[PDB]
Length: 174
Ligand SMILES: [Mg+2]
Image 1: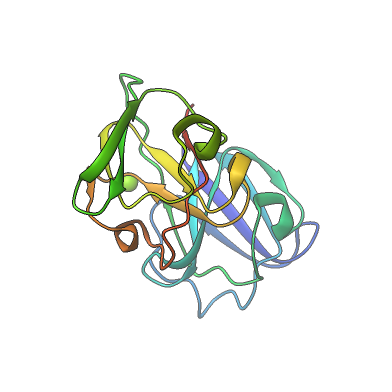
Image 2: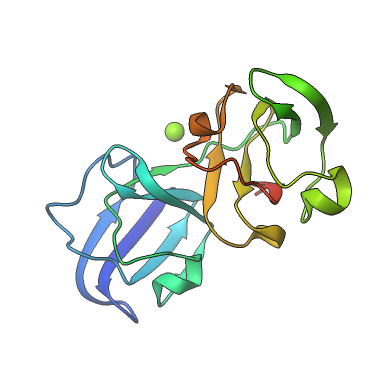
């Protein structure tokens, strides 16, 4: 089913931690993470316990360095499998201002450049009408990532961002 393996060293070496479920805190077991194998499923992995700090989405595959999942440092402490919609539906509303105010756009497609498409480089609230999405701090799915797997986000901090910068977004698909 869903299975992920974390390694302390690059190239799948060093101490290993395995998770086949949600794992809110493995910080006392693994002191650093430099490679991952996702045997099955799509996972959200997090820098700090209880799904906090930097986060990253990893589908099935082999990741011999943290840079391979766009990791921003060597620290991972928690993880959870992403629940994708069984009916495969995806739809999001993005808003210029907080609390669902200002200009709104609705889309069912990915967006590698919010500036090109919508003339914005910040998003201040969002409703995830269907499915599961990721916001990115930089264009074209680069930089820090923010998982949007809840229904409503009133302010950027609701998706884990201290900065309102969002320059691309996409769906997490099977
Ligand atoms: Mg779950």
